[PDB]
Length: 146
Image (cartoon, rainbow, N blue to C red; front, side, top):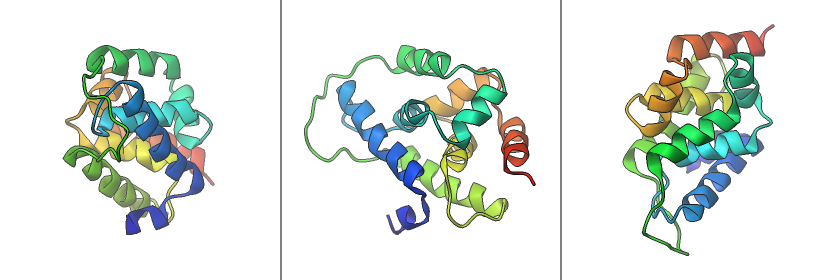
């Protein structure tokens, strides 16, 4: 959460949107799936440009995530905590950033963090759509160059 000092405005906004996505589905946790939904919803950063560059539809990503996770049965108004794997995505995102010389990270690194996490809904969707780690890293390098 000191972590969020190294997130850009848009990446912070993705995390706010993730919490909204969880509420919209009556999920009482913010999982990898919700971070990905937030990311595609925001739709205007480097992550979104990376997906579109690869021929992956943002609408397709939402449909695949929403199909897997469906609807919860825990409406809440409280703070919605992150799942342990969602917290790991955030940590991983910072390290994806540092590997490319970015201390302050935008949405491209949340995308890479999602994928690097490997095991959750987000990674499963993205890998199945062809956004695997090596390919998205290459895309992001291209969009950051230089």
